Length: 121
Image (cartoon, rainbow, N blue to C red; front, side, top):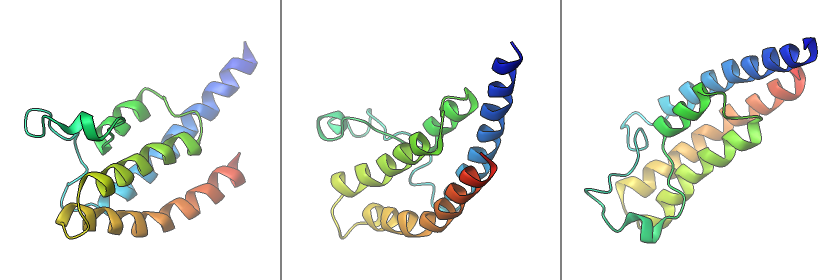
């Protein structure tokens, strides 16, 4: 139907916007600490600690399968990245400190993307 197509053009444009947002947030991780899933070969106990792992590559697979229906769902996945890190790693570590910075620096990008999604519909 024509309705289903118009929905599909909206999803596709939300996907285009979320891709730009993802690229912006990932630039705020120049050390690539959050680029890829935590290795289970190298951190075998990780799933005992963290029940829903998340990372930028995994967000990217979902993004390109148009798996985010709205900005909220996308934000949930980003927060998992940060929140998982801040639990598993202690305060005085490069990893925790890199999350705090990604959180603080991402906030601006996310502030504006919420306005653009509301605005553009």
